[PDB]
Each structure stands twice: as C-alpha cells, then as structure tokens.
Image 1: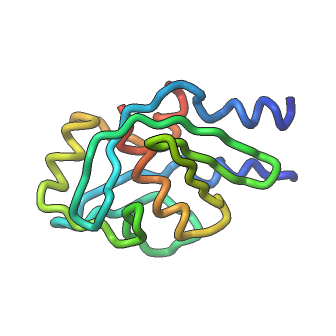
Image 2: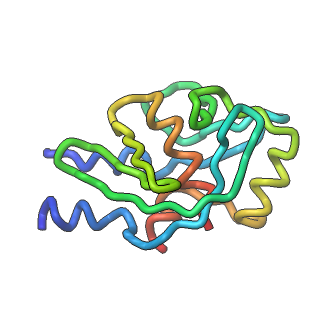
Length: 72
Length: 69
C-alpha cells in the first residue's frame, strides 16, 4: 500500500513444487517465498536455508521461474 | 511509472522441446531460453513432457495463473 500490497502479490503460504538439483535430477520440495518490491528481490526458504533471486538478472529469472511454474 | 518487477514475467510458461525444458513468454528475449537448475545448468530431462503434464494436466499454466491462486 503501495509497496506493502505489491509485496503481498507473491503468496506467503507453503508451496509444494519440484526442484532440479542438477541438470537431470529432480525432487519434490516445500518452500516459502518473500518479495521485496522496492528493489525487485525474491527470497526463497528451502531446507531451512535462504536463496535470493534478483528479478533484473536474466540468469536468476531462468532459475526461479521453473520453481514457481511447477508448483501445485 | 515506477515498475512492479513481477509484471514483465506474468506471461512466462514452460515447454519441453524433446528433453530440453524451455521458458516461453518473455518479451525482451526474441528467442526462447532454457530453464536452469539450482546449480545453473540447463535442464535436460528424459521424462520432461510427462513431468509437465503430471503437474498441470493438459491445461497450460503461466505465472499469472500461479499468482491468481
């Protein structure tokens, strides 16, 4: 409101998805996401560890999008 | 405008070209690009097409469809 509501565009609930740990290896995963719309960053919590993705960096975008798009 | 960085990703969607997992629907690319694993390698998976359909069925799924849940 405005930034606050922008941050709420990404769900806060658990996401059940699939993650490719290598080029040819995939496994089920449950994750949480946080979004900071001021600078365009998403933080993902996976196996108790933090991962960050810069939404202005094409390589991060290509890594994050398959995780979101395979979620149920 | 002050942009919402998510907006330019809302039409993104996955597709299998043989065993290669690709990302369609990104406006600034004039060509499709490969999806990357968590260790930064292009995803190549023998059961690619069956994995996609296991998740969504036959219905196509964009990022916008994910965000409206």
